[PDB]
Amino acid sequence: TAQVFAEERVRELEAEVAELRRQQGQAKH
Image 1 (tube, helix red, strand yellow):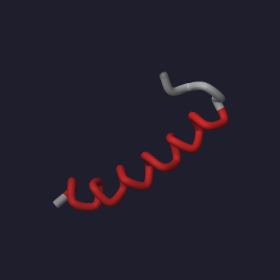
Image 2 (cartoon, helix red, strand yellow):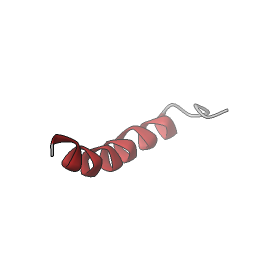
Image 3 (cartoon, rainbow, N blue to C red):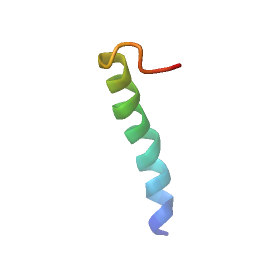
Image 4 (cartoon, rainbow, N blue to C red):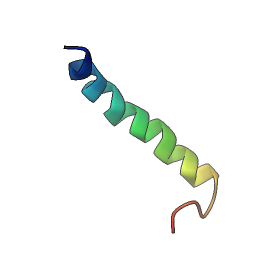
């Protein structure tokens, strides 16, 4: 289904954004 590979997508996308918070410095409170 469309959301089957989205589930494969999101997990990667998460990594892409979560590494970006790092570059934002103290972006997690």
